[PDB]
Image (cartoon, grey):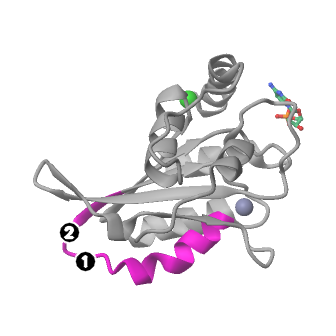
Amino acid sequence: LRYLMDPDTFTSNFNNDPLVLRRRQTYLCYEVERLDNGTSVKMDQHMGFLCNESGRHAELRFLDLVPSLQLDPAQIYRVTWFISWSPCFSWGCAGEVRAFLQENTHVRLRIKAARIYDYDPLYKEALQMLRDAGAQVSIMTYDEFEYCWDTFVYRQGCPFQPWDGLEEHSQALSGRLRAILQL
Ligand SMILES: Nc1ccn([C@H]2C[C@H](O)[C@@H](COP(=O)(O)O)O2)c(=O)n1
Ligand SMILES: [Cl-]
Ligand SMILES: [Zn+2]
């Protein structure tokens, strides 16, 4: 029912090797949980993935589709993004997400990023702006990559195969992100 990602597209876009060139696209896998007094309700209708299209970054395209999710404003939600690049500032993503979180205080956001989008001169301000708007931002580790493979990919029951250096790159990126976000 929910359309599943090609496995080579996954591997190519979520690779966290710092030397691989893959700026041209961003893949954003999302899920929404409704929190019903300590109880999480996570429905497949609120799960999917998006990439950039017509020059519009995937994060903005996620914001475009929030009305279609039909979230009840009387309820509390946690959205999680597994995203191949952390959000930018200069093409509007961090500021639109901040505005979204400020307008929708019934929604909380967790962003798990495979790599840091440092092509933007203001990338650190982007990450800090997301943190300060209440988003929990972190770097994807083995556990997250495996979850995404298992959840969003057309894997035909086949297990996640971690690429060489996955852990080393993830811990390195995590150090860099935690230094940016230190409070
Ligand atoms: N630990 C780091 C910090 C910055 N950089 C890169 C990201 C940018 O392309 C460039 C300038 O970053 P900054 O403005 O944060 O110093 O260096 C990196 O590759 N590794
Ligand atoms: Cl982290
Ligand atoms: Zn962006």
Look at the numbered discs 1 and 2 and tell me whether their residues touch, using CB distance below 8 Å: yes
Establish if 38 lies above or below 99.
above
Question: Which of the four quarters of the rendered structure image does ligand 1 lie in?
Answer: top right
| Residue 140 placement (x, y as % from top left) | 56, 34
Tell me where the magenta segment starts and ends, as one range.
58-78
Residue type of the residue flagged with mark 2 = Gln
Rendered image: mark on residue 72: 1
Tell me the SS state at disc 2.
loop
Establish if 60 lies above or below 173.
below
For residue 53, what is the image quadrant? bottom right
Magenta segment: does it hold 14?
no
Q: Is residue 21 left or right of residue 7?
A: right
Residue 134 visible here: no
- Identify the residue shown where x is 53% and y is 27%: 142
For residue 14, what is the image quadrant? top right
Q: Is residue 164 left or right of residue 3?
A: right
Residues 56 and 134: in front is 56
| Residue 107 placement (x, y as % from top left) | 35, 63
Residue 149 visible here: yes
* Disc 2: which residue: 75
Rendered image: mark on residue 6: none
| Residue 106 placement (x, y as % from top left) | 30, 65
Residues 97 and 36: in front is 36
Residue type of the residue flagged with mark 1 = Asp
- Identify the residue shown where x is 19% and y is 74%: 74
Task: For marks 1 and 2, give the CA distance.
Answer: 5 Å
- Identify the residue shown where x is 80% and y is 74%: 55
Residues 118 and 101: in front is 118
Q: Residues within 10 Å of mark 2 (few under 14, many from 20)?
A: few
Establish if 64 lies above or below 24.
below
